[PDB]
Each structure stands twice: as structure tokens, then as C-alpha cells.
Image 1 (cartoon, rainbow over the protein chains, first blue to last red):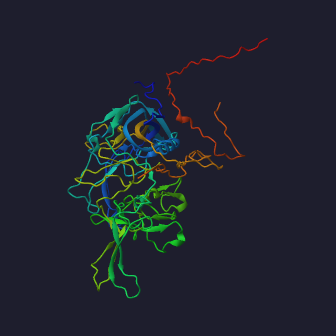
Image 2 (image 1 turned 90 degrees about the vertical axis):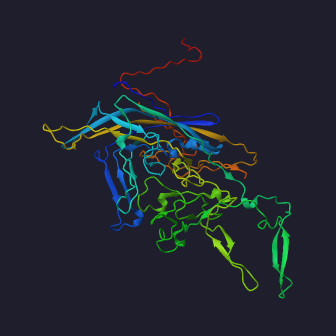
Length: 519
Length: 52
């Protein structure tokens, strides 16, 4: 451990072992100085043009954190093609972490001449929060991941958190967390940092699509032995009376047959079309949205429960706020055009789940009599019933991996609505910060705190290794499957590759459910 | 020198069977000043050269 000797290597490799796969990825980072080393109250109120639905209260800290909670940090696009073609599922088991080659630099600005020189004595402060005593920011799909392409250099985000509020004011039950109250390890150049984490048990991910549906689980050749009500009014003519008639279900009346299972839950949303001439001519993005009400606020049900996107031959329809939407390379932040975003599709789960843009079913409404016509009622929102089945939302190449289950008394089927894995004890947050170095103090005493600092920033590498567990394919199916493939004809540039200017780019969101399985 | 390589083509355009190799995908050893690097290779059998 000296100045003139490096303290690491470059490990970026993926190995396959039958039922395991170990992926390692290495990047290079740089950390600036946040808030000029100060804690700051930040808030938003109901004054101005703002509404009550968008207010907050919180604090902002000089610490920066690491986010690798997204699948493209670990999987090269060939390895994503090896994964989804040959397996019925996967879950992770354990991971590791390693920071090394810390360099700390200082900058000086004198009359346009900006000089950068080494600093060999300054430190950085890194610690992990294992016992979960902080707010958990990860798993909320923010920016700042490791880059998809290994040759790129990225910038570390900033750590800030929210508390309770009443408008732009706090309450008595609010909290303030000072991040210099936790034990941390200080590293000069020539040091390093590492730890090792172990996942708990979790269900496998369902990386398959059923080849069969709930309404078609019967034998097409044998009648049933169990009747139903088939006729109430006679058919002799116009002199009809009331009667009772019964029949057996068979091959020609397969909608009337008795069934054992129910489709999944429904929470209906509004339908919009990709052809702009077929929609209503008003701004209905928020007024017609699907919302859930929570303490005088209307939060957007995004992306809602796991429901199918569109039925057969209707690829142009999609729910307004019920799917994941991914932006292309160099898309605008506000008011991006339709040709600049990528819409995903969850048509694989229509074998069990209802379509998000249609109702669940039809129930009875009153008590029919001799002088009373019977009435029906359309169910738009249905909770759980005994005997339902459903499928969770699919995972993607650039979607998130995990999410922390909130510590409450009760929860029901704790899978994340953005897809991925549900964990009670997630991977811990890692917080990094430059230790301050003062400027020249006065010669006489002063009890004020020092506010004149030397401007610094740091850099180095990072290494993440995650081991996955697999489940192999074991089907007896005769005809060929469906595989993810490339395009055969020529193009201007190769997909999943660099530009002629050096810009990496992803053409399309890749799903996971391509193989088949019977119900 | 500098390392560059060629693939298949049809005119100034690629085809589907083309390849892209990213050279930061292989394991490599990083050297500061004061380090070094070495290896050792062995040839297979080959006929003698006819220097006559």
C-alpha cells in the first residue's frame, strides 16, 4: 500500500457453469463537491401556480451514493440473449463490491488559467448502512446508474430525502438525519474498500409465456356430466310461457362449461391510441387519468397492477399510465415526441390477466320477478377473490432489479409494480464524500465556523460481481420455439454498437418471456 | 501502431453477419510506474527451412 503501486485490477467478465452465471463489471467514476459542504432545508408550497398534489419537505446532503439497480449494468446484450432463450427463470444469490485506485485532486483558478494538480494526503469517507437506519432511495428508478457501455465515465448522484409535511411546513413527527453520525472508513490514495452481501430466499422470476388459457383448459372431445340453465321461455311461437330447461356442456358450448379458476384482479384505466386522429380532441392526460387518493393528494397509479396491455390484433392501443415507457438516445426531457420514446408491450399475460382497458365482468343488480325485468352491472374495479391466478409484470434490459418492502404490519403479494424482485433486506446503500480541507485561517481567534475551503474532487474505479442461479428448460414440445434474434438484412450501422461519433445507443427494449410452458 | 480491423461488407454497408469486438471486454493487467509485465510462449512443430 504505497503511492507508486496500484491496488487493483480490471475484472469485467462473465462465466457460465450449467446452473450458475457470475457477471463482473467495472467502471470509472468521479465525485464533485456538493452544496459547499452544507446541509440545507428544501421545500415546496401551495403558493404560486403550484398545486397541493406536488408539495414536499426534506433535506439535501453533501454525500453521494452508488446506484447499480438496473439490469444493463451487468449483462452485455449477448448475455441477455443467452439468458432469455435457454432458461425458465433466474434469481440472484450473492454479490460483492470493491473500490480501488482512489485519486484526489485539487484545482486552482487564477485569471482563466485553470490548473489541476495532485493531492496525496486528502481523504475520502465511505461507509455502508447495513442495519437500514437511513431512508432508502434506491429502487425508485432514478438516474445515475453505471453506464451500459464499459468504456464510459459517469458522475455520482447526490443524496437527499423527504419527510412528512403540511404544505411547506414540517410537523412534530418529522425527522432530521445527520450523516456524520455513522462510523465510516477514511481512505487516502493507496487504500481500498470492499464488502460482501448475501440475498435471502425469493421466488424465481417467471421468464416464460403460457401456451394455453384459463377458458380453454378442458377436453375438446368429451361432454361434461354437470348441467346448467339453458332456457327460461318456451319457443313454440308467440304464445310463450315460463319454463325451465337444462343442458350439458360440450365441444360446441365451451363458453357455458363449468370452470374451476378465475382471472386476475382488475383496476381499469383509460385507453389511448398511437394514431393521433383517433383520439378525443382535448387535453385528457391528467383529468382522465387513473388515480389513487391518499391524505388530500391525488397520486398517479403508475403503472398500476399487473394487467395485459392489448388484446388480439390491437397493437396500436395502450393504457395511458399503465406501462413502462423508455426514452431513446438523445430524447428531450420535456415534451418528447412519439418517435423519441419506446413503448413496451405486455401481451404475453393475456392468457390469465384481464386487459387493462376493459372491464372485469358483469354481475347481477336486483331481484327479478314477474313484473320486474332483470338488470346487470359492469364491474370496473375488482379486488381479490378466492381462486384467482395472475402473472407478475415482466422485467427488461434497462429496467430495475429490486425494491425494499416497506416495514408495515400487513401487505398482500409483495411484488413490485415496476417489475423485479421483492426484498425485505435489500443491498445496503453506499455513501461517499470528500473530507473538507480549510483555507488559511486568521491569526486572531474567531468563534465562527470556517467557511473558506479549497476546491477538490476525486476519482477512481468500482467493481461489482453478482452471482445468479438459473432454472433449465425441460419441455417435450415438438415444433420449433420462438427465439430472440437479430435482423438479417443490411443496415447503416450495427445495432447495440457505437455511432460514427462514439455514442453508444440501444435500439429497442428487450423483454424476457419468449419460451413456453403449459399451464 | 494503431489497431483496426475489417469485417464483411456490401459496398459501404455492413450485413447481418458482421461483427463488433469491444476490446475492454477482455481481462487486462493495469500497471503503474514500478510494475512490469511478461509471459512465455512455445512454438509447435514445423518443418525446417530449406536454406540451401
